[PDB]
Image (cartoon, rainbow, N blue to C red):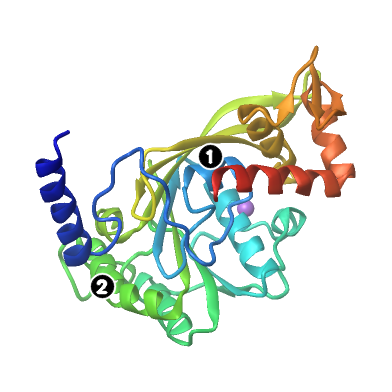
Amino acid sequence: QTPDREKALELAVAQIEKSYGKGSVMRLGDEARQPISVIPTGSIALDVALGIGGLPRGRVIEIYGPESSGKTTVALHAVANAQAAGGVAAFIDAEHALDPDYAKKLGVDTDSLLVSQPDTGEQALEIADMLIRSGALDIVVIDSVAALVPRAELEGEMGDSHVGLQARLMSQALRKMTGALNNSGTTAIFINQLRTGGKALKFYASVRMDVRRVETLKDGTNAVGNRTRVKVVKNKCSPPFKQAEFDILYGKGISREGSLIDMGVDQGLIRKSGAWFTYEGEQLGQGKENARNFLVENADVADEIEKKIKEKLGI
Ligand code: NA
């Protein structure tokens, strides 16, 4: 472009940035502006796709997809890591599907996990709000949006008529919740299905993640887990529309080790030979699984690889 023109564009981008907050406009090629702390997701691939190395703090987040997609598994990792860094976590549950043992195996401090099973939608969000305004929570997860049924509808239509009262109930709540989240620095993840009040969440959220099962991972001829794909369809902290893939193993969750290998070869830090993954002259293993297993059994070298990937990308 011309220099006389670039002055006015930078002026305009700045006015947008100042008038409506940072992230209001971005070139898709732009670098991510790194926050102090974030909540990692369990996949380095996703952390990278998110730009800022994980989920932002003090913001609303939506993770969505069909049933048995992996959306909750991603949400639970966010919880696990938030706790691992000394944070308190809450789980606002209107579905009653949570598996604590799976959550444990994946990394959650279940004993410490605050859990609430509310009577109504407004109660769910009212409780979340009170839990947030304490300033003691790092992460709160709402499972799920579709289950936030209004009092009136639960009481036999006694008190309302509008079929879209639930959407109105989300809208009101999110307006008040938004201020509480930024002040507190608390992350709120709303889990949502594809198949009630997701229209407001779509605009209030700073990150929206589209989660999908892509392919089954087999052991000879038996189902071990699923190849998962996530597109960041909305991102107010870094350029949107990035996507990542990673493995969710039944009983164990997102393989951090698999995602390190994938991004290892993606960045040329891990080389091939003949189905042989190698690192810094040493060999990790023959085939994808042996390398994965090697990194599990050698956590020190897995961290070397994690460190070596972040530094190369800022993250
Ligand atoms: Na679960």
Amino acid type indicated by mark 1 = Ser
Q: Which mark is residue 175?
A: 2
Q: Is residue 50 above or below residue 261?
A: below
Q: Is residue 164 visible?
A: yes
Percent x, y for residue 100? 70, 61
Percent x, y for residue 61? 41, 58
Q: Is mark 2 within 8 Å of ligand 1?
A: no
Contact between labelled residues 2 and 1, with CB atoms less than 8 Å apart: no
Of residues 220 and 33, the one drawn nearer to the viewer in this rendering = 33
Q: Residue furthest front?
A: 3
Q: Which mark is residue 69?
A: 1
Amino acid type indicated by mark 2 = Arg
Occupied quadrant, residue 260: top right
Percent x, y for residue 6? 16, 44
Q: Is residue 193 left or right of residue 41?
A: left
Task: Tell me which numbered mark, 1 or 2, is placed earlier along the sequence.
Answer: 1
Structural crowding at the residue carrying mark 1, measured as other residues with C-alpha within 10 Å and reported as few (<14), some (14–19) or many (≥20)? many
Q: Nearer the viewer, mark 1 or mark 2?
A: 2
Q: Is residue 248 left or right of residue 286?
A: left
Residue at 47%, 63% (x, y): give it. Answer: 35
For label 1, the SS is loop
Q: Residue furthest bottom?
A: 134
Percent x, y for residue 297? 89, 43
Residue at 83%, 44% (x, y): give it. Answer: 301
Occupied quadrant, residue 29: top left
